[PDB]
Image (tube, rainbow over the protein chains, first blue to last red):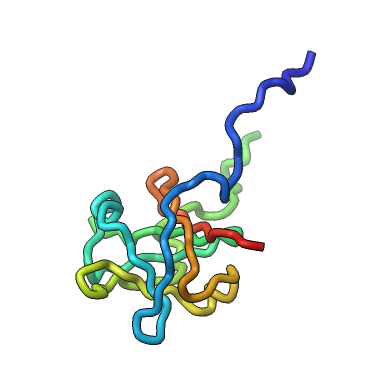
Amino acid sequence: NHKVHHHHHHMSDDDDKGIHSSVKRWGNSPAVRIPATLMQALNLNIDDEVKIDLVDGKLIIEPVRKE
Amino acid sequence: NHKVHHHHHHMSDDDDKGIHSSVKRWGNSPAVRIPATLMQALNLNIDDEVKIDLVDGKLIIEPVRKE
C-alpha cells in the first residue's frame, strides 16, 4: 500500500503569503521598510547591524547577536 | 569504530560572516540598504515587491516572482 493520498503540507515559497513589501529608493539606493513588529521580535533596533546571508538563492536575514 | 574525528562543516549562524549591514532610520521607519549586487542577482528592482517570511525566528527574504 502507498499513502500517495496523504500529502503533508504544501511546499510553495511564493504561494505562502508572508509579508509583502516594496523596495523603494532612499536617495539613490534600494531600501526596504522593515516591520517594527519584527524589529522587536528579533530584538534589534535602529543603527543595529544585521547579517545578510545569501543561502541557496535566498536571502537570509540573521541579526548580529550581541548578548 | 566511530568517526567523531570527522566533523563536516561548522554550523554557526552568527559566526559565518556573510554581509554585515545596518538598519538605519528613513524618516521614522527602519530601512536597510539592500546590496544592488543582490538586487541584480535575484532579479528585483526598485518599487518591486518582496515577501518577508518569518521562518523559525529567521527572516527569510523571498521575492515576489513574476515571470
